[PDB]
Amino acid sequence: LKITGVNIYLLKSGRLHPVLVEISTDEGITGAGEAGIAYGVGGTAAAGMIKDLSERFLIGKDPSRIEELWSTMYDHSFWAKNGGAIIFAGISAIEQALWDIKGKCLGVPVYELFGGKIRDRVRAYANGWYGAADTPDEFARAVERPLKEGYGALKFYPLAQRVLQHVTRRSMSAEAIELAYRRVKAVRDAAGPEIELMVDLSGGLTTDETIRFCRKIGELDICFVEEPCDPFDNGALKVISEQIPLPIAVGERVYTRFGFRKIFELQACGIIQPDIGTAGGLMETKKICAMAEAYNMRVAPHVCGSSLIETATLQLEANITNFMIHEHYPAFKADDGYVEVLENPPSISSGYFEMPNGPGLGAVLIKRNIEPYLWASCT
Amino acid sequence: LKITGVNIYLLKSGRLHPVLVEISTDEGITGAGEAGIAYGVGGTAAAGMIKDLSERFLIGKDPSRIEELWSTMYDHSFWAKNGGAIIFAGISAIEQALWDIKGKCLGVPVYELFGGKIRDRVRAYANGWYGAADTPDEFARAVERPLKEGYGALKFYPLAQLQHVTRRSMSAEAIELAYRRVKAVRDAAGPEIELMVDLSGGLTTDETIRFCRKIGELDICFVEEPCDPFDNGALKVISEQIPLPIAVGERVYTRFGFRKIFELQACGIIQPDIGTAGGLMETKKICAMAEAYNMRVAPHVCGSSLIETATLQLEANITNFMIHEHYPAFKADDGYVEVLENPPSISSGYFEMPNGPGLGAVLIKRNIEPYLWASCT
Amino acid sequence: LKITGVNIYLLKSGRLHPVLVEISTDEGITGAGEAGIAYGVGGTAAAGMIKDLSERFLIGKDPSRIEELWSTMYDHSFWAKNGGAIIFAGISAIEQALWDIKGKCLGVPVYELFGGKIRDRVRAYANGWYGAADTPDEFARAVERPLKEGYGALKFYPLALQHVTRRSMSAEAIELAYRRVKAVRDAAGPEIELMVDLSGGLTTDETIRFCRKIGELDICFVEEPCDPFDNGALKVISEQIPLPIAVGERVYTRFGFRKIFELQACGIIQPDIGTAGGLMETKKICAMAEAYNMRVAPHVCGSSLIETATLQLEANITNFMIHEHYPAFKADDGYVEVLENPPSISSGYFEMPNGPGLGAVLIKRNIEPYLWASCT
Amino acid sequence: LKITGVNIYLLKSGRLHPVLVEISTDEGITGAGEAGIAYGVGGTAAAGMIKDLSERFLIGKDPSRIEELWSTMYDHSFWAKNGGAIIFAGISAIEQALWDIKGKCLGVPVYELFGGKIRDRVRAYANGWYGAADTPDEFARAVERPLKEGYGALKFYPLAQLQHVTRRSMSAEAIELAYRRVKAVRDAAGPEIELMVDLSGGLTTDETIRFCRKIGELDICFVEEPCDPFDNGALKVISEQIPLPIAVGERVYTRFGFRKIFELQACGIIQPDIGTAGGLMETKKICAMAEAYNMRVAPHVCGSSLIETATLQLEANITNFMIHEHYPAFKADDGYVEVLENPPSISSGYFEMPNGPGLGAVLIKRNIEPYLWASCT
């Protein structure tokens, strides 16, 4: 086939700003992908990156040469070498859509191309359930719904607050750090001793206070703590892992095999959380997970965007041997202004997700829903 | 003062696509800045990032609190933590504009605020003088112009065709040609001219070491980015295996990014770009940190006249300054767009320090107006 | 699909003893694979391992679940953990057949499944061209033919005629080693790439001495300068010699190569899809190598099958360097052609096969006499 | 003497598939040896290796030259360099037989050749006494028998079902159950019995550490193979994070393989198998090295009566011997095949040292003949 056009969509879906790409071919086969910059600051940047990459590397090209196309964008974009979230989110979006096209061409799910499936379903943990909870009591109150819905695991950010604003300059008042502990204690009390709890610090405090806080909640049986320190500082990550009794998980802000090599050699993390929308794509993430196995590590893919990226993530989760658990934000669909991008989005069933079976990513975009958000078209 | 609006300009200037930002305040004092994504793929991403950062963090705020503004964008953009070129080029352009405003408010150049100047002019090396040369003969012939114009140092890309290396591989013929280009340049320039070779990533470790050793006899000032910026392991091994001083930094960002370079103690020169490293103060901090590791600085600059002028603010002030980078041919491209009424003018390989308040730069609105990409008010 | 049977062939082809495997499915689609224990001592060990793996893990399984099967064999064979050449060559052969089956089901070459091709052909260096040369002049005389055939690179074993005994050689033997390399460079000319395989070399000190002594002869790379067991010696040597180093022939899986990667002492790895764990495992190993600024020169020495299979990987990995080929092996006395369409060189280049799966067609009649075991 | 023939036997003895070898000499004196591939997947492979080695290195050679023979097989089999269990299991079997012959020729136990005995008896721990136990109660129930039999230490696999962990993952229920099994066992055996827990690779580093800490209060003698034998990085990390002593070695081969373990300084016990590590002398060498690292040895043994008897030879000689491993419930298995005319018999958890020449073990040709796999002459 030949790529004849690429459309970029910059959506407004509730509290998120999903960035989607659609690759069209002369055969009429289309591919869909999503850049993992649905939250934070940079959505327009991601859209613009997909535009620049498409106008420079995709139009008129044969979509079947995925590895070459990836290699080309890496070698000749200039900014990919030691590149960050924006360049690789743009590349990830494109790569996903390319595997989607290949899967459609061969009439099978991408995971079959990757070597088949290892599981037909995956357990998931709930995120976003805490809503606008602030006090320990409100946090304890919010655990009911998710648990009743079948989730056996919960994740939350005890240092943050809805405004979701994370720590300012790695520091907090003794009162806020106290409240943080009371939040975790409340969730453990209201959830019971059998529910798995994950604490995301999204950067944490300075090393000393982070270790102090982590040790303090150790008695509350924590599955793992996410990003206990700034992703920029791997020295701290190693020091923290040697000083706390909680398992550590990172990866949400690490990109490609090249970026993860730095995490692997530290041997301070037992869990990695690559995002297929930022780590480099489906195959790049598969490669990352494969390397992780060489370091006795499990994988808990990070996902937070439209239904597309979540469905695309199931593709990889059906195939990686060192899978741990899926991340799901059930409340996002209730957001005022939520925009459903798939005709058949993934549906949870008592905390479990079935593996999609349609060709490629096994996802059909509702063009009518995203059309109002068309940001750019390259031909 | 209060920020009343921000304008983003995505230009088409010859072979470049400079990205500029202009910050307006209620009292009429404006600040200008440039994101260092003027080449490569991502100009629109940079413009988009400045737009997103501006709409979320700048309108209505006091521009005098530069450190707090920078800190806020780092802390709450989410993508700044272990961030890359796009997020930091956006932050950098904004930061530059804030310093421009502060200098204009205080009535002095930014370098006065940074601790005063240490030099009145800076020596520069010429880049882009090779044009389209391919054969060793064409390269040798291209050295004439820059040397006549006063430059005492030259940089070029022996492995490039600019298109750099594909998959860290090159045929034996291209590698020999590479060596022949360097030799031809050394022969045509004489033993006094300083030559810098930029490999922009190079080949695999073994082949890069081989090539660097082979040109060692040609007296190279330094080899730039001998390996992929992603791989600091290779960088360390290469430094221990070649007789040439190494320089990197063009694709490293913030003090946090450079820390990884400093601890390797493999490079003697760093090349941060104030348009991507984080801004003027961030780069000053990076340079100060480099001094604790016995290194000097050769700031990377490649964009419009604005970013080059702003870089001079830094070079007038840092203690470990080595040399300034200039592309004299860029202004001859077709479609070149001049953004300043008084662009930096070389005089025998030397640039005088700007003396106006702030960045000492004045935009020609007429020339950039056509490229207005977005407005945030 | 469902796996219905496995046939194992222990061949006697010339100087080699290729071990092949054929997996049948309930729908007539069969896959072929080859264990990289075609030389050295252990061909029967390899055949027996494929027999044990097949009997315990293959019959009745869905072949499309390649990752799961690999995982199962690794997790429950017991000997795979920190496992060696036998267990992984067996697993490798089986994994190759599963990909062969998958490609045939989807109607495309395995490389399309891996992400498409990056190149349509690969250059190669010649091996075994030296024949039975002992003296320098004989080696010098042996360079004629391969060059005539169009090869731009040559590989040989100056220390080997077998390999080094107890990491020791006489001064006479060491000077002769230098003389052969010198004779080859002189007879080949300056524009020919030379690769030297020490297959373990001597003790660190003597190996460093030899490597330095031949540095003036412009060597592309030196293969296995020390015993594969001693990674400490490997690092020391890399820091002390002026030659690029290449290893991997006797290193297995991602877990095995991790140890090589962390050394950052080599610039080239040489995994064998027949021993490193398989096609996908080797692709994963190659992807890892890119993170360490290394390129790959796959090791291949078996029947036409494994060479054709290796071409599947070389058409897709981004850090490919060069292909290994033994032209003389087909002229061997007792050579058994296993493919209906053996890979044929053309002035130093091999085109990429285009058939579905491994793009290789077995000649059942030529291997049937070597059927070693059947599992159903 | 001269080697005239080699017979390889692929046995079917209960749950195991013992692989034995018999080297014959032109003088009638023969030697017995066993390759440690009695379990797992690869018995046939092991037999195939001994056949290949014998046909290429043994027939017609002088057997008194054991070192030379070992060295020849290592140097010219090609796959021995950085070799694994199969190649070295084959070499071990052969080497065991060579010492058997030399000992018989000199009329003394091999341990006398190695420097004499240090002990006349060794205490052993019970393994396989759990049978098909699954629930905590069943494991508890199971301790009675071995303890009645006079055993002072027990070893089990709390994570197993035997089938070990799949993809280093377990449900919280299975992990929770694992804990109860260990606790139920400590409760039933009393505080005086030593308990060994083999994880055969365990889970991922993080979960493994948590589990090891949880059972810490149960006074564990040591945890075996807490992580994949392939990952020595994880082994070191785990050793620094848990309160339990660590033991490994079942899947590490030769001095060259153990060097990697020793340099980690992560455990206090190694468990080499003379049937896989390379042989009796090779293992003695390994044990001698381990002393230089303040470690003790608990030889791994799980095969026919032959390899267990040969292991005793070693255990009567090494200075840093810790304890012997025995499987009392294998002699009861349906299909069990006794290979020795005089197998080792426990006496209240104690084994006396064999006094016969060579390995001090006489084979029952009638019992292994049905399993002749190959013959080389």
Image (cartoon, coloured by chain):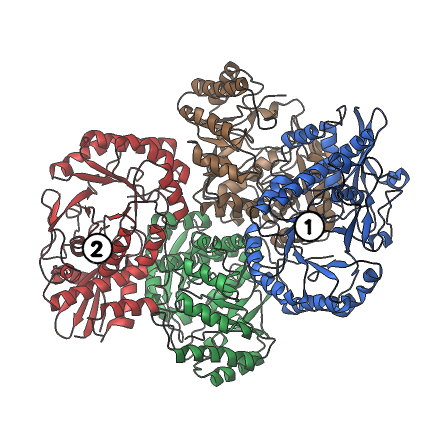
Chain colours: A brown, B blue, C green, D red
Q: Return the residue nearer the eye: B158 or B122.
A: B122
Q: Is residue A212 visible?
A: yes
Q: Amino acid at mark 2?
A: Lys
Q: Return the residue nearer the eye: C53 or C375.
A: C53
Q: Is residue C363 visible?
A: no
Query: Which one is closest to the eye, mark 1 or mark 2?
Result: 1
Q: Return the residue nearer the eye: B242 or C320.
A: B242
The answer to whether dots 1 and 2 both sit on one chain is no
In terms of secondary structure, where does tag 1 sit? loop
The chain carrying label 1 is A
In terms of secondary structure, where does tag 2 sit? loop
Instruction: Tell me the distance, in whole angstroms, between the alpha carbons under discs 1 and 2.
Output: 63 Å
Q: Which residue is mark 2?
A: D12
B175 vs C289: above or below: below
Q: Quadrant of residue D114?
A: bottom left
At label 1, counting other C-alpha atoms closer than 10 Å, the crowd grade (few under 14, some 14-19, many 20 or more) is: many
For the N terminus of chain B, give its image quadrant. top right
Q: How many marks?
A: 2
Image disc number at residue A252 = none
A164 vs D288: above or below: above
Disc 1 to disc 2: CB gap under 8 Å? no
For residue D89, side relative to residue A268 (left or right): left
For residue D12, side relative to residue B66 (left or right): left
Image disc number at residue A78 = 1
